[PDB]
Image (tube, rainbow over all chains, first blue to last red; front, side, top):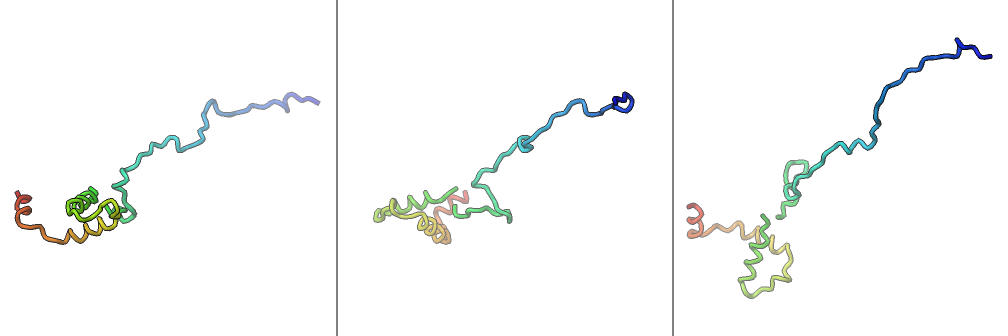
Length: 49
Length: 49
């Protein structure tokens, strides 16, 4: 049978938040001009020019 | 600076050749052999001014 004291509780949570997926939309991304691009040795690739 | 157009005009004014069927390698290979030559005395003294 229904006991009131054994069947009443006090629940706790947060007030508000927001969940963000797609974390990489907060990243601004630019690129050096492709004639000035270098490899790992800090020496330019396509030395043919 | 890309030096194809310097050596391309080199072969236009030597009137014998047809430049439209010369590929790109021979223009950048003619470069690397023409770079080892010393500059003559009249065009070099202009540059030092």
